[PDB]
Image (cartoon, coloured by chain):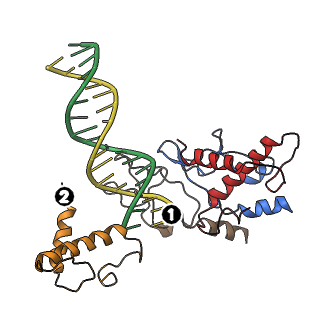
Chain colours: A brown, B blue, C red, D orange, E green, F yellow
Amino acid sequence: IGKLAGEGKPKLANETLVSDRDELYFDAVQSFIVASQAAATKASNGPFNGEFDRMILRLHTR
Amino acid sequence: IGKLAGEGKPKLANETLVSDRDELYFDAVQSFIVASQAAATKASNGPFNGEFDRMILRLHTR
Amino acid sequence: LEQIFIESNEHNSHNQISQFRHAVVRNKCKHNPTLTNLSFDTPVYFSIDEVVTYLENMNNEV
Amino acid sequence: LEQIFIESNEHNSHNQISQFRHAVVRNKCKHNPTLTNLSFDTPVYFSIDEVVTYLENMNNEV
DNA sequence: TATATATATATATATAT
DNA sequence: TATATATATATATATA
Protein backbone atom coordinates (compact mmCIF):
# COMPACT_ATOMS: atom_id res chain seq x y z
CA ILE A 1 0.00 0.00 0.00
CA GLY A 2 1.20 3.49 -0.81
CA LYS A 3 1.38 6.25 1.76
CA LEU A 4 1.46 9.36 -0.44
CA ALA A 5 -0.93 12.21 0.23
CA GLY A 6 -4.44 11.17 -0.72
CA GLU A 7 -3.49 7.58 -1.59
CA GLY A 8 -4.20 5.67 1.61
CA LYS A 9 -5.41 2.78 -0.53
CA PRO A 10 -3.80 -0.09 -2.43
CA LYS A 11 -1.97 0.64 -5.67
CA LEU A 12 -2.12 -1.46 -8.82
CA ALA A 13 0.75 -2.21 -11.18
CA ASN A 14 -0.75 0.46 -13.46
CA GLU A 15 -0.68 3.06 -10.68
CA THR A 16 -4.42 2.73 -10.15
CA LEU A 17 -6.22 2.73 -6.82
CA VAL A 18 -8.30 -0.05 -5.27
CA SER A 19 -11.29 1.53 -3.54
CA ASP A 20 -13.22 -1.62 -2.54
CA ARG A 21 -11.55 -4.97 -2.02
CA ASP A 22 -14.64 -7.12 -2.41
CA GLU A 23 -15.08 -6.15 -6.05
CA LEU A 24 -11.60 -6.89 -7.42
CA TYR A 25 -9.68 -9.45 -5.36
CA PHE A 26 -12.20 -12.07 -6.46
CA ASP A 27 -11.95 -11.68 -10.22
CA ALA A 28 -8.36 -12.73 -10.88
CA VAL A 29 -4.77 -12.27 -9.79
CA GLN A 30 -3.38 -8.75 -9.68
CA SER A 31 -0.04 -7.00 -9.97
CA PHE A 32 1.13 -4.30 -7.57
CA ILE A 33 3.95 -1.77 -7.21
CA VAL A 34 7.41 -2.20 -5.77
CA ALA A 35 8.01 -1.39 -2.11
CA SER A 36 10.34 1.55 -1.61
CA GLN A 37 10.96 4.44 0.76
CA ALA A 38 11.64 7.05 -1.89
CA ALA A 39 9.40 10.03 -1.31
CA ALA A 40 8.20 10.00 -4.91
CA THR A 41 7.28 6.29 -4.87
CA LYS A 42 6.85 5.44 -1.21
CA ALA A 43 4.99 2.26 -0.36
CA SER A 44 4.87 0.05 2.72
CA ASN A 45 3.88 -3.56 2.96
CA GLY A 46 0.53 -4.55 4.34
CA PRO A 47 -0.84 -6.15 7.45
CA PHE A 48 -0.96 -9.81 6.44
CA ASN A 49 1.90 -9.70 3.95
CA GLY A 50 4.24 -12.66 3.96
CA GLU A 51 2.24 -14.63 6.52
CA PHE A 52 0.07 -16.66 4.14
CA ASP A 53 2.84 -18.47 2.30
CA ARG A 54 2.51 -22.16 3.12
CA MET A 55 -1.28 -22.26 3.32
CA ILE A 56 -1.74 -21.38 -0.34
CA LEU A 57 0.44 -24.26 -1.47
CA ARG A 58 -1.10 -26.74 0.95
CA LEU A 59 -4.59 -25.86 -0.25
CA HIS A 60 -3.77 -25.87 -3.96
CA THR A 61 -2.35 -29.34 -3.39
CA ARG A 62 -5.27 -30.71 -1.40
CA ILE B 1 12.82 -15.32 -4.46
CA GLY B 2 12.77 -11.95 -6.22
CA LYS B 3 10.19 -9.27 -5.50
CA LEU B 4 10.90 -6.75 -8.27
CA ALA B 5 8.36 -5.68 -10.84
CA GLY B 6 6.80 -8.44 -12.90
CA GLU B 7 9.24 -10.78 -11.17
CA GLY B 8 7.02 -12.52 -8.66
CA LYS B 9 9.05 -15.70 -9.05
CA PRO B 10 12.45 -17.17 -8.20
CA LYS B 11 15.79 -15.96 -9.47
CA LEU B 12 18.94 -17.95 -10.14
CA ALA B 13 22.61 -16.97 -10.21
CA ASN B 14 22.41 -15.83 -13.85
CA GLU B 15 19.42 -13.47 -13.61
CA THR B 16 16.82 -15.76 -15.13
CA LEU B 17 13.34 -16.30 -13.73
CA VAL B 18 11.42 -19.58 -13.54
CA SER B 19 7.84 -20.46 -14.42
CA ASP B 20 7.22 -24.14 -13.61
CA ARG B 21 9.37 -25.63 -10.88
CA ASP B 22 9.08 -29.21 -12.07
CA GLU B 23 11.08 -28.56 -15.23
CA LEU B 24 14.54 -27.84 -13.85
CA TYR B 25 14.72 -28.56 -10.14
CA PHE B 26 15.14 -32.30 -10.69
CA ASP B 27 17.97 -32.30 -13.23
CA ALA B 28 20.82 -30.86 -11.19
CA VAL B 29 21.48 -28.71 -8.16
CA GLN B 30 21.41 -24.98 -8.76
CA SER B 31 22.73 -21.89 -6.99
CA PHE B 32 20.83 -18.64 -6.50
CA ILE B 33 21.79 -15.07 -5.66
CA VAL B 34 22.10 -13.84 -2.09
CA ALA B 35 19.27 -12.29 -0.13
CA SER B 36 19.30 -8.51 -0.38
CA GLN B 37 17.05 -5.54 0.22
CA ALA B 38 18.28 -3.01 -2.34
CA ALA B 39 15.53 -1.26 -4.27
CA ALA B 40 17.33 -2.34 -7.44
CA THR B 41 18.21 -5.89 -6.35
CA LYS B 42 15.30 -6.92 -4.11
CA ALA B 43 15.66 -10.55 -3.07
CA SER B 44 13.86 -12.20 -0.16
CA ASN B 45 14.13 -15.64 1.32
CA GLY B 46 12.00 -18.55 0.36
CA PRO B 47 9.16 -20.14 2.22
CA PHE B 48 10.67 -23.52 2.99
CA ASN B 49 14.33 -22.53 3.27
CA GLY B 50 16.21 -23.97 6.20
CA GLU B 51 13.71 -26.46 7.52
CA PHE B 52 14.78 -29.53 5.56
CA ASP B 53 18.38 -30.13 6.59
CA ARG B 54 18.44 -33.40 8.52
CA MET B 55 16.33 -35.81 6.51
CA ILE B 56 18.63 -35.16 3.57
CA LEU B 57 21.60 -36.64 5.41
CA ARG B 58 19.46 -39.39 6.86
CA LEU B 59 18.42 -40.43 3.37
CA HIS B 60 21.93 -40.16 1.97
CA THR B 61 22.93 -42.50 4.76
CA ARG B 62 20.23 -45.12 4.29
CA LEU C 1 29.95 -36.73 16.45
CA GLU C 2 26.98 -34.42 16.90
CA GLN C 3 26.76 -35.37 20.56
CA ILE C 4 30.37 -35.27 21.69
CA PHE C 5 31.07 -31.77 20.37
CA ILE C 6 27.84 -29.87 19.69
CA GLU C 7 25.49 -30.04 22.66
CA SER C 8 21.76 -30.15 22.04
CA ASN C 9 21.37 -26.56 23.22
CA GLU C 10 20.99 -23.49 20.99
CA HIS C 11 18.36 -24.82 18.62
CA ASN C 12 19.39 -21.96 16.30
CA SER C 13 21.83 -24.38 14.71
CA HIS C 14 20.71 -24.45 11.06
CA ASN C 15 23.88 -22.68 9.97
CA GLN C 16 26.17 -24.33 12.50
CA ILE C 17 25.49 -27.96 11.68
CA SER C 18 25.42 -27.43 7.94
CA GLN C 19 28.74 -25.65 7.78
CA PHE C 20 30.27 -28.10 10.25
CA ARG C 21 29.47 -31.04 8.02
CA HIS C 22 30.62 -29.10 4.97
CA ALA C 23 33.94 -28.54 6.70
CA VAL C 24 34.50 -32.09 7.84
CA VAL C 25 33.85 -33.41 4.36
CA ARG C 26 36.56 -31.32 2.76
CA ASN C 27 39.06 -31.90 5.55
CA LYS C 28 38.54 -35.60 4.96
CA CYS C 29 38.94 -35.33 1.21
CA LYS C 30 42.23 -33.51 1.63
CA HIS C 31 44.20 -35.93 3.80
CA ASN C 32 42.96 -39.06 2.02
CA PRO C 33 42.83 -38.38 -1.72
CA THR C 34 43.47 -41.87 -3.07
CA LEU C 35 39.90 -42.73 -2.14
CA THR C 36 36.69 -41.50 -3.74
CA ASN C 37 33.05 -40.88 -2.87
CA LEU C 38 33.66 -39.78 0.69
CA SER C 39 30.98 -38.71 3.15
CA PHE C 40 30.35 -37.38 6.63
CA ASP C 41 30.48 -40.72 8.43
CA THR C 42 33.15 -42.34 6.29
CA PRO C 43 36.00 -43.45 8.58
CA VAL C 44 39.00 -41.49 7.39
CA TYR C 45 41.27 -39.13 9.26
CA PHE C 46 40.71 -35.44 9.92
CA SER C 47 42.30 -32.73 12.04
CA ILE C 48 39.75 -31.25 14.41
CA ASP C 49 42.10 -28.33 15.01
CA GLU C 50 41.87 -27.46 11.34
CA VAL C 51 38.10 -27.59 11.61
CA VAL C 52 38.37 -25.03 14.39
CA THR C 53 40.63 -22.81 12.33
CA TYR C 54 38.17 -22.90 9.45
CA LEU C 55 35.15 -22.13 11.59
CA GLU C 56 37.02 -19.18 13.07
CA ASN C 57 38.09 -17.81 9.71
CA MET C 58 34.39 -17.91 8.97
CA ASN C 59 33.44 -16.23 12.23
CA ASN C 60 35.54 -13.23 11.22
CA GLU C 61 34.80 -13.34 7.50
CA VAL C 62 34.62 -9.94 5.82
CA LEU D 1 7.98 -3.93 41.27
CA GLU D 2 9.30 -5.62 38.16
CA GLN D 3 5.85 -7.14 37.84
CA ILE D 4 3.74 -4.10 38.66
CA PHE D 5 5.51 -1.30 36.76
CA ILE D 6 7.39 -2.93 33.87
CA GLU D 7 5.16 -5.00 31.56
CA SER D 8 6.86 -6.01 28.31
CA ASN D 9 8.13 -9.14 26.60
CA GLU D 10 8.30 -10.81 29.95
CA HIS D 11 12.12 -10.93 29.84
CA ASN D 12 13.18 -8.83 26.87
CA SER D 13 13.75 -5.35 28.35
CA HIS D 14 17.33 -5.36 29.53
CA ASN D 15 17.89 -1.67 28.89
CA GLN D 16 14.79 -0.17 30.45
CA ILE D 17 14.96 -2.47 33.44
CA SER D 18 18.49 -1.44 34.31
CA GLN D 19 17.91 2.25 33.82
CA PHE D 20 14.78 2.09 35.96
CA ARG D 21 16.79 0.44 38.69
CA HIS D 22 19.48 3.08 38.46
CA ALA D 23 16.90 5.82 38.73
CA VAL D 24 15.32 4.39 41.86
CA VAL D 25 18.65 3.61 43.48
CA ARG D 26 20.08 7.07 42.94
CA ASN D 27 16.84 8.75 43.97
CA LYS D 28 16.51 6.93 47.27
CA CYS D 29 19.72 8.50 48.54
CA LYS D 30 18.40 12.01 47.96
CA HIS D 31 15.36 11.78 50.22
CA ASN D 32 17.02 9.74 53.00
CA PRO D 33 20.61 11.01 52.89
CA THR D 34 21.58 9.89 56.39
CA LEU D 35 21.54 6.16 55.64
CA THR D 36 24.48 4.35 54.06
CA ASN D 37 24.91 1.62 51.45
CA LEU D 38 21.38 1.73 50.10
CA SER D 39 20.32 -0.84 47.51
CA PHE D 40 17.37 -1.31 45.20
CA ASP D 41 15.55 -3.87 47.29
CA THR D 42 15.92 -1.76 50.41
CA PRO D 43 12.66 -0.43 51.92
CA VAL D 44 12.83 3.35 52.14
CA TYR D 45 10.87 6.19 50.59
CA PHE D 46 11.16 6.76 46.85
CA SER D 47 8.96 8.96 44.69
CA ILE D 48 7.74 7.67 41.35
CA ASP D 49 6.73 10.96 39.76
CA GLU D 50 10.32 12.13 40.05
CA VAL D 51 11.50 8.99 38.28
CA VAL D 52 8.98 9.41 35.49
CA THR D 53 10.08 12.97 34.87
CA TYR D 54 13.71 11.90 35.08
CA LEU D 55 13.29 9.42 32.26
CA GLU D 56 11.18 11.90 30.34
CA ASN D 57 14.17 14.20 30.55
CA MET D 58 16.68 11.59 29.45
CA ASN D 59 14.48 11.10 26.41
CA ASN D 60 15.13 14.52 24.88
CA GLU D 61 18.81 14.83 25.80
CA VAL D 62 21.21 16.49 23.37
C1' DT E 1 10.39 -4.22 22.31
C1' DA E 2 15.22 -4.65 20.21
C1' DT E 3 19.16 -5.00 16.26
C1' DA E 4 20.25 -4.25 12.18
C1' DT E 5 20.61 -2.86 7.42
C1' DA E 6 18.70 0.39 4.61
C1' DT E 7 18.14 6.04 3.82
C1' DA E 8 18.44 10.79 3.41
C1' DT E 9 19.57 16.06 4.49
C1' DA E 10 23.40 18.61 5.85
C1' DT E 11 28.23 20.06 6.30
C1' DA E 12 32.92 20.80 4.63
C1' DT E 13 36.30 20.23 1.02
C1' DA E 14 38.25 20.30 -3.75
C1' DT E 15 38.32 22.31 -8.20
C1' DA E 16 37.26 24.37 -11.88
C1' DT E 17 34.76 28.65 -13.88
C1' DT F 1 33.02 32.49 -6.84
C1' DA F 2 30.22 28.75 -7.92
C1' DT F 3 29.69 24.07 -8.58
C1' DA F 4 30.20 19.58 -7.67
C1' DT F 5 31.46 15.68 -4.57
C1' DA F 6 32.17 13.06 -0.11
C1' DT F 7 31.48 11.49 4.76
C1' DA F 8 28.72 11.81 9.31
C1' DT F 9 24.33 11.25 12.06
C1' DA F 10 18.95 10.46 12.52
C1' DT F 11 14.40 8.48 11.45
C1' DA F 12 11.67 4.42 9.53
C1' DT F 13 10.45 -0.58 8.14
C1' DA F 14 11.13 -5.27 8.41
C1' DT F 15 12.20 -9.92 11.24
C1' DA F 16 12.74 -12.57 15.04
Q: Which residue is drawn at the image coordinates 31% and 85% (left, top)?
A: D4
Q: Which residue is drawn at the image coordinates 63% and 69% (left, top)?
A: A55
**Residue B20 appears in the figure:** no
| Observer-nearest of C19 and A37 | C19
User: With respect to residue A55, does B1 lie above or below?
Assistant: above
Viewed as shown, does residue C46 lie left or right of A29? right
Residue ID for mark 2: D61
User: With respect to residue A23, does D32 lie above or below?
Assistant: below
**What amino acid type should be assigned to the residue bearing mark 1?**
Asn
Quarter of image, res A45: bottom left
Give coordinates of residue B54: x percent, y percent.
Answer: 73, 63
Give coordinates of residue B57: x percent, y percent.
Answer: 78, 60
Give coordinates of residue C26: x percent, y percent.
Answer: 75, 45
Q: Secondary structure at mark 2?
A: loop
Residue ID for mark 1: A49
Viewed as shown, does residue C40 lie left or right of B36? right
Q: Which residue is drawn at the image coordinates 33% and 81% (left, top)?
A: D2
| Observer-nearest of D26 and B24 | D26
The crowding category of the residue bearing disc 2, from other C-alpha atoms within 10 Å (few below 14, some 14 to 19, many at least 20), is: few
Q: Which residue is drawn at the image coordinates 28% and 82% (left, top)?
A: D41
Give coordinates of residue F4: x percent, y percent.
Answer: 30, 24
**Residue C15 appears in the figure:** yes
Q: Chain of mark 2?
A: D
User: With respect to residue A13, does D52 lie above or below?
Assistant: below
| Observer-nearest of A47 and B59 | B59
**What amino acid type should be assigned to the residue bearing mark 2?**
Glu
